[PDB]
Length: 57
Length: 57
DNA sequence: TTCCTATGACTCATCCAGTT
DNA sequence: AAACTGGATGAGTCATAGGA
Image 1 (spheres, chains in turn purple, yellow, green, brown):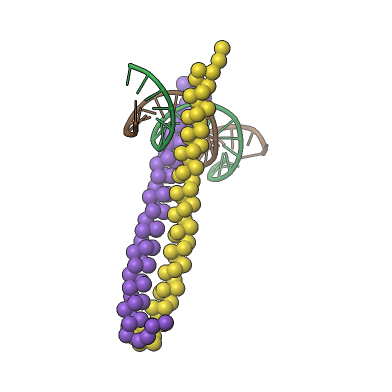
Image 2 (cartoon, each protein chain N blue to C red):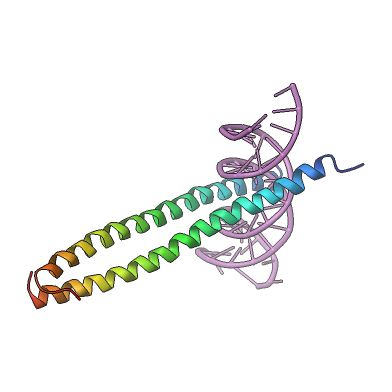
């Protein structure tokens, strides 16, 4: 192992934990986009229900 | 002396430029929708507070 | 066989952070 | 210390999977 050799198999792992970590950062941004659409589904229905027992505007 | 292989890299290297613009744009694309959706749903939460005050809970 | 791209993995040159 | 020690980012290149 030169310090370049040591260094390379170690950088190679820090490039790794980051692809793994970059995978998670988008799988979550998919979920915050999911739940927000389930919340807009239930919320505009809720409005149409209380809307009905009063007026249309 | 030359480029057999310098054509295979200058093309693979375009392809990695390309594959990486896609991931860049699905990521900014979803994040705008997290801001957008967020915004619709506060307005709707307010309209629901209001119609449950016009009428009730 | 043979060719060709799209994506994972590894290397390189930076650059940044903690730490004393 | 804008230079120790070692991790971490961006972009080219390598190894492979899939496609035709």
